Image (cartoon, rainbow, N blue to C red; front, side, top):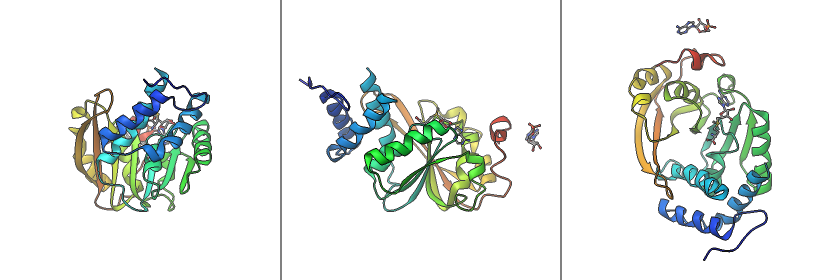
Length: 239
Ligand SMILES: C[S@@+](CC[C@H](N)C(=O)[O-])C[C@H]1O[C@@H](n2cnc3c(N)ncnc32)[C@H](O)[C@@H]1O
Ligand SMILES: Nc1ncnc2c1ncn2[C@@H]1O[C@H](COP(=O)(O)O)[C@@H](O)[C@H]1O
């Protein structure tokens, strides 16, 4: 079984892995195979298949929190090649997504993916978080924000919280270990207008690797001091 090949897209095996992992998360990914297969093709053009199908499914674990109903404006901060934002947008088309990265080549890739996949209401944007969050067009302008593989929580919270409207929420995607990053976090969140929401432990669908989704709730406006200038949260983190 699963012998069929594909010159520029997911193989029969890769399609089946994606569907199976999807069903484990509670998702029916059949309507979205072509979109994911195209995205896979784009990545290859820029084990191989399995690993990508895992970036897809890791991104889709966001759907294990019911945070994504309706035309919410969502920021994917530090999106790289479009993760977790592109899979999210594929499976929740009503979301109005902005995908940010400081590296032009990555933003150029996301922009191309958006067009090739024919996504509507997704924009890639080149910029730094610390600078974009001081513009009225982005500061406290999002209902949701997400980030994967960007920074430790104490730094990442200073980067994410300023983009959220009050009442909004951010998800920091993390791996198997979060105790150390969480322990000193609540007092820093309060300085930012945030508070710690749920920390959901879950297992990645095909591999069983441990993951945590860390929810940051926006409870009050962020003081003008934050975020600090580029590089400063990283070198003098709040915790
Ligand atoms: C390790 S990559 C992870 C990319 C993607 N989120 C993923 O998980 O596949 C982190 C990305 O964050 C970007 N980045 C880090 N700090 C940033 C900042 N302060 N503002 C904008 N982009 C940032 C980097 O340029 C890089 O492409
Ligand atoms: N230990 C520290 N904790 C927090 N901020 C600092 C610290 N040392 C310097 N700063 C501030 O961080 C910014 C850059 O400082 P520097 O790292 O000396 O370039 C400046 O606004 C300083 O006022």
